Image (tube, rainbow, N blue to C red; front, side):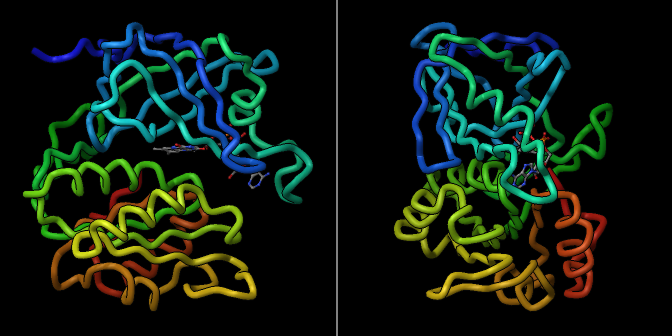
Amino acid sequence: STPAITLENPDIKYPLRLIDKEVVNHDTRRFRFALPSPEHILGLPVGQHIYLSARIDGNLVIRPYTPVSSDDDKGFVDLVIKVYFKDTHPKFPAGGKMSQYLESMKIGDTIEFRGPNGLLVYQGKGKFAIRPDKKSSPVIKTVKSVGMIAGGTGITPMLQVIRAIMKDPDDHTVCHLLFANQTEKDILLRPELEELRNEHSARFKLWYTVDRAPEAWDYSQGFVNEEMIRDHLPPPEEEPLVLMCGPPPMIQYACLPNLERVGHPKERCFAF
Ligand SMILES: Cc1cc2nc3c(=O)[nH]c(=O)nc-3n(C[C@H](O)[C@H](O)[C@H](O)COP(=O)(O)OP(=O)(O)OC[C@H]3O[C@@H](n4cnc5c(N)ncnc54)[C@H](O)[C@@H]3O)c2cc1C
């Protein structure tokens, strides 16, 4: 039999109760929410995400999140969240709306989840189903490798796919991740990524860049660029699928122009 799914209809909002909040570091949290029963699963296909919605200071706010849990987890869903506090970043004095609202929640408070959502679904063994828009059928494409470029919070869509491939010992897809962040301190999910590299190096290639580097730094510094793409994603001759998730200026200025310079078809580079 299969477990009961939580996300039965994508137009329904499901208020889920907050049961645990881990302080991972000063500005990183893991929030665990109970599903409707301990035996439920979320019902989130690999490749897709949920939305959280709430009335925050009187206004509706909706944001996408990819859990760090999977449909293997019974009874809960986990979100890893970067909290963007006010009065930290000079360009963002107000800080972030949903992330500060999550940080404010008390154990036992609920928040609405919806899903699944997203134009890409991973069907296993290299096969991706990608819709051009929501109203259209998917193009099924089967690849031998996947380039992944994440910035900041954009890691969790990548991690979800990486995890799904590595857990299938008969999935020979090779993932190459290039992960950009502001600083070393701001990197999310580093232990988790490095665990995967330790266990699955043949199938999982990991590289970091940081806008500004620490004194002791073994990886790249600067924004994603042509060299990093040549050095840390599969070559275009191999026809990899390229996935991206990061802030709009990163995608627009750093990723697409440089994917094109290397020769990847820019039109086929998918942004979550
Ligand atoms: C498919 C998908 C999955 C995602 N999964 C996750 C996830 O698992 N975890 C997660 O944390 N986010 C995730 N995100 C990002 C998430 O949707 C929100 O963008 C994020 O929570 C910030 O929203 P907010 O309402 O707090 O900030 P907003 O109010 O929307 O602020 C706008 C932007 O301002 C910038 N900003 C604000 N304050 C600061 C600051 N102090 N320093 C640096 N920049 C700042 C950030 O770039 C921010 O996104 C995902 C996004 C996508 C597209």
